[PDB]
Image (cartoon, rainbow, N blue to C red; front, side):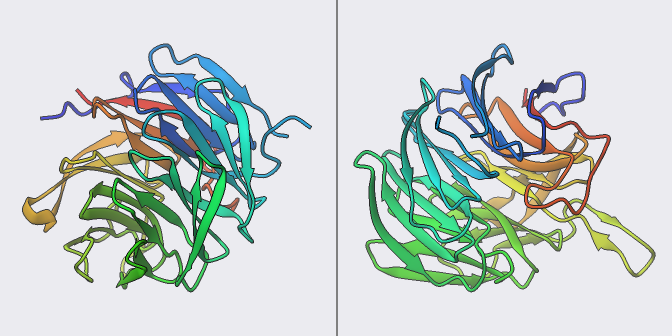
Length: 330
């Protein structure tokens, strides 16, 4: 089994001045990039917890508005960061040198993923579009349409395909790019706010009604759905579920992680055929869990925490720390 980590195990990296919005772990597991509502990007050493580089709020390169999303290529070469200025900035991940700025989105960039094994980048946006870029050639390829509202998130693995979470449109969409085809799955579970691939044929999503869903990429209804996955607050009969702010999966395994603002990160195991989600443990962690990523090794989980939700200022948890938390999974 996995030993349930406690506060005495969790390394809390401090330095962002406002809520963390997103992060990535480098493929080699040696570093973390995080971004926050302070508009900066920080590169951290996993091993020491020290800062390796800081890209400040921005004619030096950098972001003038919140970074909402980031992705790193599978060879570790490129970092992409997407912001509320409609921009995707591309960086040399080793040096943090700015390489390019992709323009073309008409509203905030809200999801990014590289196609594994390539330098092909997929983005999505509040402008309701999905875009395809080639980072090696600094080129724009094409735009795909279908979502009916601002898109919340995007993931991809090795196939020429991405999956998106439609937010208030209530859909998860599968974009089969060379096939010029689009599969639309209906969640019937409020706003679909986060998504992550588990393997090439399965994914996990989280919704603002508190539900966590497992999907097969070719079946139109969830294979599993865990209601109120982070529990409840409120009066008897009038309960309000904790909304799901982040989800992560450990590639090619049955391990999934979920985050809300319920004071814990939850680890789950997917049952045979992905037809059931079973809770493994609660990891104590106060605040908005705005980002979750497993290490490549699966030996640690990284959480991006904020006093506030990554998308707005509606709620503040004053007891939380705006931190990048390294959670060991032993």
